[PDB]
Image (cartoon, coloured by chain):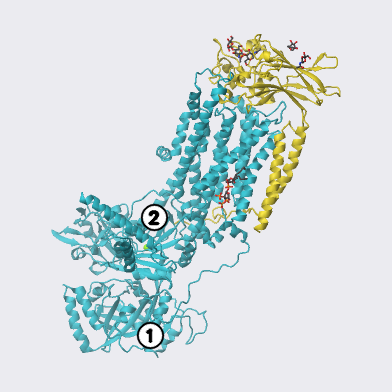
Chain colours: A yellow, B cyan
Amino acid sequence: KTRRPDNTAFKQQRLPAWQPILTAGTVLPIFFIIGLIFIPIGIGIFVTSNNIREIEIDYTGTEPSSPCNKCLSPDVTPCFCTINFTLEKSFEGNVFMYYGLSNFYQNHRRYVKSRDDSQLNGDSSALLNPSKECEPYRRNEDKPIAPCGAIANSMFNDTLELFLIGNDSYPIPIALKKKGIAWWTDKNVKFRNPPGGDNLEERFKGTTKPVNWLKPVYMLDSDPDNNGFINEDFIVWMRTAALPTFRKLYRLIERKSDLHPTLPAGRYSLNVTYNYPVHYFDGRKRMILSTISWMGGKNPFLGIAYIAVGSISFLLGVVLLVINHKYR
Amino acid sequence: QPNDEVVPYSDDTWQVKANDRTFIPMNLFEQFKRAANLYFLALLILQAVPQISTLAWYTTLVPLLVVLGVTAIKDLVDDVARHKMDKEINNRTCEVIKDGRFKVAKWKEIQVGDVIRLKKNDFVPADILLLSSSEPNSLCYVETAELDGETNLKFKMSLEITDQYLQREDTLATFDGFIECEEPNNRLDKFTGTLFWRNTSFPLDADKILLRGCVIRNTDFCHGLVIFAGADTKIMKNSGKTRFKRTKIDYLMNYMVYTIFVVLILLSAGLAIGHAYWEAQVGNSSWYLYDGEDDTPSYRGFLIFWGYIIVLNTMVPISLYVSVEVIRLGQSHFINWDLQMYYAEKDTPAKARTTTLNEQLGQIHYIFSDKTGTLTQNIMTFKKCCINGQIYGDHRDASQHNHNKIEQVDFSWNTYADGKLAFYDHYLIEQIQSGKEPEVRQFFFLLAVCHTVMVDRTDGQLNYQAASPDEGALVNAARNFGFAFLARTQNTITISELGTERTYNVLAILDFNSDRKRMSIIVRTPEGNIKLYCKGADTVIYERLHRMNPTKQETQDALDIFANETLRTLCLCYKEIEEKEFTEWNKKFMAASVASTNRDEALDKVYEEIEKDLILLGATAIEDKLQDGVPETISKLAKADIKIWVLTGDKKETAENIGFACELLTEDTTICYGEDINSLLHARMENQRQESFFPPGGNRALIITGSWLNEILLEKRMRTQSKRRLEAKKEQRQKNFVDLACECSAVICCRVTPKQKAMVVDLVKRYKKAITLAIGDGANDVNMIKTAHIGVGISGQEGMQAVMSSDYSFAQFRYLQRLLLVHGRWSYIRMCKFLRYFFYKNFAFTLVHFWYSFFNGYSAQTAYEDWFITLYNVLYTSLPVLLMGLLDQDVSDKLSLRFPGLYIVGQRDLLFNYKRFFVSLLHGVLTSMILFFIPLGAYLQTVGQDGEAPSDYQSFAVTIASALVITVNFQIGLDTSYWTFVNAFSIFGSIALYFGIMFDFHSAGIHVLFPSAFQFTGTASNALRQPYIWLTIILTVAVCLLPVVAIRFLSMTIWPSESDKIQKHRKRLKAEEQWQRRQQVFRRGVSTRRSAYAFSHQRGYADLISSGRSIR
Ligand SMILES: CCCCCCCC(=O)OC[C@H](COP(=O)(O)O[C@@H]1[C@H](O)[C@@H](OP(=O)(O)O)[C@H](OP(=O)(O)O)[C@@H](OP(=O)(O)O)[C@H]1O)OC(=O)CCCCCCC
Ligand SMILES: *[C@@H]1O[C@H](CO)[C@@H](O[C@@H]2O[C@H](CO)[C@@H](O[C@@H]3O[C@H](CO)[C@@H](O)[C@H](O)[C@@H]3O)[C@H](O)[C@H]2NC(C)=O)[C@H](O)[C@H]1NC(C)=O
Ligand SMILES: *[C@@H]1O[C@H](CO)[C@@H](O)[C@H](O)[C@H]1NC(C)=O
Ligand SMILES: *[C@@H]1O[C@H](CO)[C@@H](O)[C@H](O)[C@H]1NC(C)=O
Ligand SMILES: [Mg+2]
């Protein structure tokens, strides 16, 4: 027919190849180095996570005898809830203040898509023409909602304050920092204010506030760098959670200049303006104070999982070794 | 009643006047034929409905357009490859009349009724009518080795009127002849017609019609008038109907695509039910989940059912078909490239001319082979002979045995001898030269006279035109041994006896016929004595020997030795005729010749009168040379558990000889014929009016003629129901034969039509549900090549009839070793490895949405980025599995020929069942549980919580997609056994490509251009910088793969496969003895156990020399 095929390794189907064989001496080592490397990691994660100082206060007050059930039915919409908690052990270094919501499906598909990123990106066209996705919250009466969406509308609007109850019994306020709680990319890339002008008043012209919001997006904060679409608390909320039970960074309690602990052990009071209702759908609001760890945060599951997987790998290796020896 | 000597074409008006004679349909083809392509078009519609859409239309078009584009690209090269196949090999040209003179024309520029012209060794382009020819009386000799298996030449005659008026070219052009004949039929043994010319009617018969598969032999030129052309030729009518061949796994994959569809509907319906329930006691109380749409909870569940069809759509693959056919396309090129299947003698490589039937080569159960031209070279050589009880042919020197290593005999002392005779025996030469044993001289004088061959001396080269290759072998052999047939005349022959020019007067040639099994010649010596010389079968000749035959016992022993060596044997004899005895017989002989009323039987009666007391000269032995490696190939494919059946159109004697030479029939086998087979089948009928037909331990073979094949298979209102018994009675008989024939070690069907060949193949496909391979050459094998699951066409010859209709095409039968044991065996392993992993990586990827449903309110929120689902099946997991399906090798090609037992794995369909399919779905299901619930455990707690905390859905999505890509690309490395550089590059390149593209999508630069499409800006940078995110990804991959490694090791340690055992002792294997024929099986106790007689020849040649028809 045609000429002779050319003698190449690929076409003659003899490419230089490594032939791995799952021999007794090739798989058993990987079942022991994994076992001997995963166990120490699990010990490190487990012990380090346990060393993290954390307190979690559930201020939802859904069950009676919690001293702010009065805020489940706030006849006067200013409702203030006060809870006394004690830090048996002092907190050292930077401490992070979080608020947690349980049974809050912020990953619902109808919810996740209810936003206009082109609007949050500071696009002039998308400011006055919110997308169809944020449909129920596009326009309030005649002009469009500036942060359109079910996500922006349902923003966490509780206010949390911490006071240190000293020996004098006078509550000492604790400084809370609301800056640098969001992703740098979210602050400086994803979220931008509408272009032009120098005052947010004129920039957000011809747009309503979200129906659930008390005040417009103009004055989310007094700082010109923390109001508008670039507000830290707003951007933290906009970052939807992966699971129904989550927590979102609220404030940074910076390390004190003095050598004393940032949150010395003693009596504390949590003064929260109850604004966010979650008890309708069996939700739970929480306040979490946690100290910084150079191994991320407190993840005992990863510590235990590495011990379990590492332990089983060693156990499998011994079982495989016995089986191989019998069938040698 | 059934006749063992004929091909039963019976059990299976036209008018001729002389000289008066690309992308739109392919996309649609792959859409409708494939249910999955319409499935992905339906999803596009469901993805464009905002009420139900859960994934962007990008998520399906991008994979679909790539899949559609790649399929179109493959279909183009197949279209171009097929065009090249047809064009480059259909370059056949014949001379036709369309102007005042002949001119070269293609075989396609042939109309019904145009005068043509052929030369020596020309294939006949169409069924023609002999009008004139070079040799006298407008004869024409044609070999029909392509129309049937017959290896001898047949003479054809023209009309006595066309012979004497259409000799010149000028009159052929003006020939205005009108022919009425039957409509195109398949039956090649007669032709009913009439030629109306010169105001006269001339009836026609098949002796005047040259058929398409014929080849002109020993004729300088012959002119014919085309009667039929193209598909109207009787040989094309015998070609079957082309069918669209599909593999055993092609049907399987359709069932599996329907199984994943059913699973997808059921999972979506359950998840839709859960959402309807979730929206009742949770979703309706959630103020933040208010969409201003008065949708009832059950309507939301109905409305999300289409959402989960979209989300879980990747369960059914979008690249399964392209991946399967891209793998087969590459696997088909390894056949075209194999240098071990390349025949350098004819410059013919193997050709995978169908790129769609590849893994089926690794599943063959039965091989149905042709004989003439497929198992043989169409060469016959004189090997041995017994003279006066002394066997000649062994390696000998001088007058006594000295050593085995003997040089070729020197024939320089002979003037006419040439090198065609490779004889290693010098003792015979002294007997011829010395002359002390004149019967040795007399033995080879017989071979130079008892033939009926013709001699060509037009230029002094003394070429022999033998119609029987046996005669050509014997006449050539005697020519080398000093007895050369020089010239022939109507009455005389001019044999030269060692240079002595002696002219004998032929008084009678007792022609050959199949039932006669011998021929004789009576010649008058120059002295004046009359001698009768006869050669033929040992059985017939031993019935006509003189009482005093001292060499009878010794000659019988030699015939047994020749028979045990798989050679074709003839017995030589003669007698002295007295002058008074001959004239008495001659008077009766002449009467039977002139008497035309019963000439055939009249001549036979007088033949027996003179062949009464014959003195035995000796015996000959002729080898019908097989193709090299044929017995080796049959022994190895028998170790692969493949049964080889020989279906040939050649005579029973030739078929049985090649069966013994091929080692298919040994001296252990007991051979059953149609007479015996029919009796056994009958006994099964009255017995039932299943017990094994034979004892299990015996060795048996069937030699079945076409007449007996029809006899045993019954293929020789009241009408309505009466047919059901006739059809049901046949169907029971059809099944009984298949069970009988499949109970035999070997089966040979001889004298069968092209339809019968396909019929036998079809019976095994039906009643055994077996995968069948048919290999052959010539147009009589096209029917079974098209019928079989795989059809191989022996290429490299000059006629390409079986090549065009075949799936594969190599030149040598021995290349069937590598086609099945190497290429098919690997192709099956590689196809099943691909399917085992391909359905793993699609379930592991898609079932993550299923587990995330239990934490997002059953809202069909994807667990991945929108653009990860777009590129997963085309970028992140496409290349590595393709490279495995093209490069995997469990053992070496040389080590897979050494162990044909590895082939049985694919015959039993062990590497991919419905069970192996569901085990890979369970593998993907369990992988998706870990790919989700390990990240979920980490994310349920603190995962790097600071300002840049990746505890959100996007970080969750990136983490699971990262672990999935590493896991499914590390699984394909555990599956791979042949780790090439490209295999390593694809596995790590696929993981590297995912990270490279992901960081490009999650970038500030692209977000500014269009924020709407890309929502994951900055997620990869934040998520993959955290130690817990990488500690979570590492843990997920380890838990996904460590159990797999333990299972693979335990399975290999406790239940190692045949490949595993060979690899363990690969370096400790050194004993591989080459195949050897059974050199000696001689025994004592029976004078005759089997007759090795075989002689391909026909009637009518003696009558040509007897008259002046063939003498010029
Ligand atoms: C650790 C306990 C195993 C739990 C699974 C229970 C075991 C199970 O159902 O099957 C395991 C599945 C299937 O995935 P696999 O393909 O890895 O399992 C097959 C494996 O390929 C064997 O080796 P091999 O022939 O492929 O070289 C095969 O041997 P053989 O062909 O001779 O029979 C056998 O077939 P068989 O089962 O006999 O039909 C299966 O065990 O996935 C896994 O390999 C691990 C999945 C789990 C991974 C995540 C961990 C939960
Ligand atoms: C903090 O956020 C909650 C919701 O996350 C706010 O409660 C919501 O307040 C809006 C009004 O601003 C209510 O919308 C509509 O108000 C009209 C009065 O014009 C009322 O008649 C309707 O019932 C309608 O809902 C919305 O229902 C209400 N939602 C809930 C769950 O209470 C709250 O006002 C916010 N507080 C601050 C200080 O930002
Ligand atoms: C919490 O502290 C406040 C002020 O210190 C006090 O009035 C209130 O009774 C305390 N409640 C409980 C439950 O200790
Ligand atoms: C709690 O905070 C509110 C608002 O900042 C303030 O008016 C009140 O005095 C604080 N202390 C309480 C409620 O005990
Ligand atoms: Mg043939």
* Residue B896 placement (x, y as % from top left): 54, 59
Q: Is residue B216 visible?
A: no
User: Which residue is most to the bottom?
Assistant: B436
Which of the image's four quarters has the C terminus of chain A?
Answer: bottom right
Q: Which mark is residue A65?
A: none
Element class at badge 2: helix
The answer to which of B330 and B571 lies nearer the viewer is: B571
B876 sits left or right of A69 in the view: left
Q: Residue at x 33, y 77 (%)?
A: B537
* Quadrant hosting residue B33: top left
The answer to which of B580 and B849 lies nearer the viewer is: B849
Which residue type carries mark 1?
Gln
Q: Which residue is mark 1?
A: B553
Q: Which mark is residue B765?
A: 2
Element class at badge 1: helix
The residue carrying mark 2 has its beta carbon less than 8 Å from ligand 5: no
B805 sits left or right of A179 in the view: left
The residue carrying mark 1 has its beta carbon less than 8 Å from ligand 5: no
Gap in angstroms between the C-alphas marked 1 and 2: 49 Å
B71 sits left or right of A173 in the view: left
Name the front one of labels 1 and 2: 2
- Which is nearer the N-term, disc 1 or disc 2? 1
* Residue A163 placement (x, y as % from top left): 78, 16
Disc 2 sits on a residue from what chain? B
Disc 1 sits on a residue from what chain? B
